[PDB]
Length: 130
Length: 130
Length: 131
Ligand SMILES: [Mg+2]
Ligand SMILES: [Mg+2]
Ligand SMILES: [Mg+2]
Ligand SMILES: [Mg+2]
Ligand SMILES: [Mg+2]
Ligand SMILES: [Mg+2]
Ligand SMILES: [Mg+2]
Image (cartoon, rainbow over all chains, first blue to last red; front, side, top):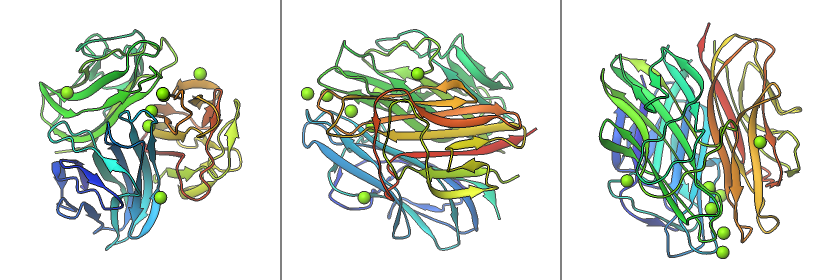
């Protein structure tokens, strides 16, 4: 039983990994809120989804890509000329081997720190085990 | 086998619970389209996801939060200065006990009434039973 | 039975055509066809599908992307921005499917973004339960 769901507390920017440290669910402790990465332990098929809210009132564009190890497996953008709140979200189904790391990487722009509202989220779970 | 998927027919506003009464799937009849809430019967881990379309041509901001019982477990915002259509969407994986209610509540703003087109949606299913 | 797929959009789409997600990352069992952009059901049961369609930026203000079962709209989504900014038409569904049923993502007006290999616009899904 592998499943996790965490939210983003603090604001982020640039090209850094998003540390979702508002952890709500973490069966097996395979997600690390100190690095914001999900480490695969059992080979198999996994679903991941992420929602990243852009910082409002400061900036027009923000990118958030889901990476496996050091390869982009999903890309997303939030854009608005009037600096409005908008979401960079995406979902993936991937096969993972032991040691594989899955995380959400910013690719430019500013993310919102939602404190306790859990605006920016990272969630996932194993569908099938090999 | 617990799983459901329902859409929103009527427009909503303010801070009311979103009653997705255009029901497509409801294994176990655990979702109530009359209250718009999903009642847990078996303790375990559950996936939920929601997409709420903002009312266009009237208002600039709309909030939609996924609440468990009476606690926010996900927040979302749609915002556009030009009153354009935009989405407040989010997903969660949570542990649930029997009697727990999970639903999508507006937290300010105006929601779009999509009739039968299923623009605004709420779906979910159990991953693991304890 | 392990039934699951996840594909991204390489080329641009527009009008009212089905989105051919031809950047396939996962396709256990080959029930999704990237040449038609359709998921054909073989095993009766309950399936989760989700799609994210990025609107084309700098050209157009509105875009629709609907998830269709057979030839029936089972989910609709819109992306809109007056300043022609990037925005998403995304949605998720849980549906019961019989063998032969086709599930795909169709544009319903507007222009979709071609992300090449970046996987900006995506279509994914998987079986939860088999009958
Ligand atoms: Mg927008
Ligand atoms: Mg990128
Ligand atoms: Mg404007
Ligand atoms: Mg709130
Ligand atoms: Mg606008
Ligand atoms: Mg968006
Ligand atoms: Mg339509």
